[PDB]
Image (cartoon, helix red, strand yellow):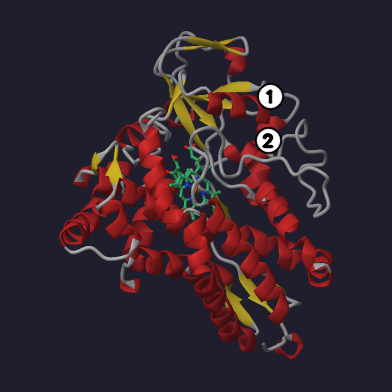
Amino acid sequence: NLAPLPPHVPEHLVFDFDMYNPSNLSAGVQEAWAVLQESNVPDLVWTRCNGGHWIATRGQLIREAYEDYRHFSSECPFIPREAGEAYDFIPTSMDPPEQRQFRALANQVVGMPVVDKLENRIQELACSLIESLRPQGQCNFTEDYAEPFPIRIFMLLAGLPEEDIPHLKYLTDQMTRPDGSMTFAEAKEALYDYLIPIIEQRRQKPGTDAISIVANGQVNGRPITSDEAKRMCGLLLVGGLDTVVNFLSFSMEFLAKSPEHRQELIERPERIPAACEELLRRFSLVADGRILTSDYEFHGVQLKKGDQILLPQMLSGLDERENACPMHVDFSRQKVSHTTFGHGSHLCLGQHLARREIIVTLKEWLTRIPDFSIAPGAQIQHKSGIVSGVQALPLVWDPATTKAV
Ligand code: HEM
Ligand SMILES: CC1(C)[C@@H]2CC[C@@]1(C)C(=O)C2
């Protein structure tokens, strides 16, 4: 389902990539997207899929477009257009200067200071989950570790019942990796039904949780509105439920397949943080966009007001012009260049929490479970979308090779 070419699009600029179902998915998700960077593909292409939209293919253009909020507005950040249209999350659906007062509040909630406070719980949960798994000699990493670990911390942070997980997780999934089961708006409404009561409750009778803070915060010297609060919280949820979760599976998938990588981290722990940047570069997983506020000529291509453009965060680090041998994982690269956490005014506030959960996982897993692999005859499937993922990740190990801590 290809939409008819708009008149202003030169036919030589056509490259029909489906962000929801790219061709090479079998090869791995990052490999499926990287087809965009082959020598046959222009720098800026038009895909007829998902209603028709631009895609910038190179780290340079992604960064520029990301910097330029004047032309590339955040108002309609998701493709397809109906989804970008229904999208009303704060601070993400706002541009500067308006975005600023909102970002400042979200920061209060997720920023450095919070990570520092929550450090010991993260470590405690990680060790507990791992130890519980260790003697089994087998899990479902995605369900057994990658889901609980990050989500239970977010639930803790947010002061929401662990009971809600399955329901929230479904809705969040709908937004980034749409099933056909529900439309963006529907999904958005459902999450909103969830949140509304809670905010009301935390407006009246505040706690110390992130929802209590967000609901009672000040923005531009006045108190936040319930609607505003609902709209930030919504984003906090999707951020919390849908990101680190998927990241961890790619990383673990790679570690299960690369013994030499595991050992390097065991022997030279000082490398973990370098390894973390390298894995964030290679297993980058986010692709959203922007909308043209006006007619604009960008690197010689005429964009029309209202055109949407995908600016795949994932792609910058995979760009050979930015990283030599991009598909190769090298913990000792002089310069790991990526935009995994975004670029421009919208740079990820949750980045600090994400790095903390990654590095803890790597250190604590390797400690107890040094030697593991993907289960014989398991075919790992990736998924594509606003946030990519791994369907399931069956691992096996000999318990006798494990170490209790
Ligand atoms: C591997 C993990 C993560 C990645 C790859 C990631 C990626 C991103 C990307 C690429 C953006 C920018 C979007 C744009 O410019 O439209 C974004 C923004 C944001 N992320 Fe993260 N994120 C991660 C984890 C999280 C966490 C754990 C949270 C907290 C719950 C979170 C909260 C946010 C927020 C609030 C923003 C928007 C800030 C603003 O618009 O000023 N993210 N993230
Ligand atoms: C692109 C993102 C990864 C970022 C945090 C959650 C997400 C889906 C958005 O709506 C902004």
Residue 263 in sight: yes
Disc 2 under 8 Å from ligand 1? The reply is: no
The answer to whether mark 1 and mark 2 are in CB contact below 8 A is: yes
Mark 2 lies on residue:
35
Locate residue 284, reporting x and y percent: 62, 47
Q: Residue at x 64, y 28 (%)?
A: 57
Quadrant of the rendered image containing residue 61: top right
Mark 1 lies on residue:
41
Identify the element where label 2 is drawn. Answer: helix
Q: Is residue 125 above or below residue 347?
A: below
Direction from residue 115 to residue 332 in the image, left or right: right
Q: In this view, does 389 lie above or below 343?
A: below
Q: What residue type is labelled 2?
A: Val
Quadrant of the rendered image containing residue 76: top left
Q: Residue at x 81, y 68 (%)?
A: 259
Identify the element where label 1 is drawn. Answer: loop
